[PDB]
Image 1: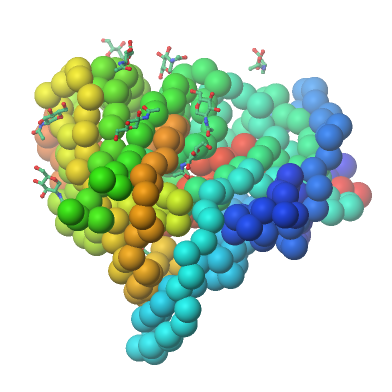
Image 2: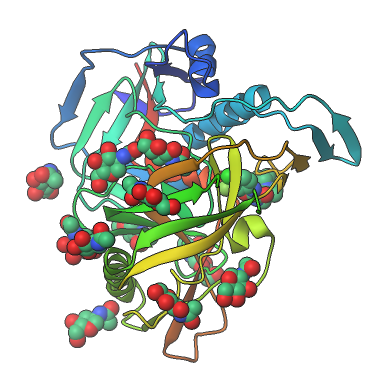
Amino acid sequence: VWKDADTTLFCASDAKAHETEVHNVWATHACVPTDPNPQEIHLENVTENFNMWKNNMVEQMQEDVISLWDQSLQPCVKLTGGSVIKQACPKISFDPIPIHYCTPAGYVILKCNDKNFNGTGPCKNVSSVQCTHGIKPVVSTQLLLNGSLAEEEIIIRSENLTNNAKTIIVHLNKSVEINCTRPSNGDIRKAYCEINGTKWNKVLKQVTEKLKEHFNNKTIIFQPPSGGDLEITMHSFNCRGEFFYCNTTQLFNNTCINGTITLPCKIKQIINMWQGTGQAMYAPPIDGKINCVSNITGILLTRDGGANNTSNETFRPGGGNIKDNWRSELYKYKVVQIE
Ligand SMILES: O=C(NC[C@H]1CCN(C2CC2)C1)C(=O)Nc1ccc(Cl)c(F)c1
Ligand SMILES: *[C@@H]1O[C@H](CO)[C@@H](O)[C@H](O)[C@H]1NC(C)=O
Ligand SMILES: *[C@@H]1O[C@H](CO)[C@@H](O)[C@H](O)[C@H]1NC(C)=O
Ligand SMILES: *[C@@H]1O[C@H](CO)[C@@H](O)[C@H](O)[C@H]1NC(C)=O
Ligand SMILES: *[C@@H]1O[C@H](CO)[C@@H](O)[C@H](O)[C@H]1NC(C)=O
Ligand SMILES: *[C@@H]1O[C@H](CO)[C@@H](O)[C@H](O)[C@H]1NC(C)=O
Ligand SMILES: *[C@@H]1O[C@H](CO)[C@@H](O)[C@H](O)[C@H]1NC(C)=O
Ligand SMILES: *[C@@H]1O[C@H](CO)[C@@H](O)[C@H](O)[C@H]1NC(C)=O
Ligand SMILES: *[C@@H]1O[C@H](CO)[C@@H](O)[C@H](O)[C@H]1NC(C)=O
Ligand SMILES: *[C@@H]1O[C@H](CO)[C@@H](O)[C@H](O)[C@H]1NC(C)=O
Ligand SMILES: *[C@@H]1O[C@H](CO)[C@@H](O)[C@H](O)[C@H]1NC(C)=O
Ligand SMILES: *[C@@H]1O[C@H](CO)[C@@H](O)[C@H](O)[C@H]1NC(C)=O
């Protein structure tokens, strides 16, 4: 017998003890080796209720990533609470690695295995595991990168679709590579991201049809953010330690519903910390070809209000709350206490 409960989890990874890469260094001192032969018991005729939007696991992973960033990515100048903190800003080696989250004795993680599970409600096929799958602490906005893919159909996730204030999580079932590069040899901060239009437009079309099922077949329209900070109005992410802000206006237009989509990007040194502490400044970009090839596995959308009396539903790319990022991976997990 068991019951829903919250306990301090521990992490596990395959980090290299000799790697200077920040993630490997952190997991080396904060995590333990992964289990080569992990056990997984499938519970038959067992119904369990999940709620990705109220999962303490998310808060804990958030706490780790914050700690990891505080120890690895300390800015030269930190502006928070009216206070000004000045420190060293040494360039580091940055590349996220899979992090497993496990439960201690007396506790076990329940995993929903329903192909089209949407994060909330009862789960028919449930199994018990000691640790979650390897999850990369990839911090980004608008587009979810290097995440897990849906096994069957594209899944729309939301704590309450009827409420436009609640962020929407689109879980893709097919990856779409996005190639971002900062050429060496001008503007050392000017960069660009290349996406396969044909591949993207088709996926975006599938996402559209999917949204129709959830919005009574209302016309689905995409539009670029109306306002807000750059971290939200643009696809912000970290590549090789550099903060990239990409203009995603060519991705979210409703005309192509076929060549190579080239997004105008730019590396920023001054960023609005996702930890919600304030502003932080980092050193200028390093030299050489800064390139990161990521797989788009999800999209964060915010729906416009005041469209009740119309047949249109406008969706814009959003983000800001990195917790939603962890939810897109921890949705099928929950901790229970055993007795
Ligand atoms: O500034 C951001 N979000 C708004 C905060 C304010 C207060 N709040 C935190 C209490 C939870 C959300 C942000 O996401 N920055 C950001 C920075 C770097 C990257 Cl690579 C990125 F993808 C996003
Ligand atoms: C999960 O249970 C359903 C019936 O409720 C079954 O059809 C399916 O095969 C099980 N797992 C999957 C997704 O294969
Ligand atoms: C990118 O996605 C592809 C599947 O489309 C996968 O083979 C590859 O391992 C992914 N790379 C990552 C997650 O870094
Ligand atoms: C992705 O999901 C959609 C439904 O949302 C489905 O029509 C499509 O076949 C899926 N694609 C793949 C490659 O499974
Ligand atoms: C998820 O599935 C449950 C099944 O009861 C449903 O009640 C809920 O509306 C779904 N959530 C979304 C975001 O579609
Ligand atoms: C979902 O959002 C709508 C609109 O704000 C609200 O009226 C409704 O109470 C919400 N549903 C739940 C279950 O809270
Ligand atoms: C990524 O884009 C650059 C152009 O900036 C190109 O030279 C490179 O071959 C691309 N990589 C892949 C794997 O498409
Ligand atoms: C773009 O994607 C399509 C499939 O959607 C593929 O057939 C084509 O080879 C891709 N183009 C490039 C330049 O890789
Ligand atoms: C959308 O339209 C299709 C085809 O008429 C219909 O089968 C389906 O019930 C509709 N979905 C809605 C209104 O959610
Ligand atoms: C994104 O780029 C487009 C290019 O037409 C531009 O019009 C728009 O102002 C840009 N948006 C932001 C957030 O700067
Ligand atoms: C929409 O996206 C396509 C991608 O090829 C781009 O060519 C076009 O200029 C965009 N339309 C806009 C920004 O109005
Ligand atoms: C996504 O994964 C690829 C392959 O490991 C990696 O090269 C790239 O840096 C990752 N992208 C981000 C945004 O971390």
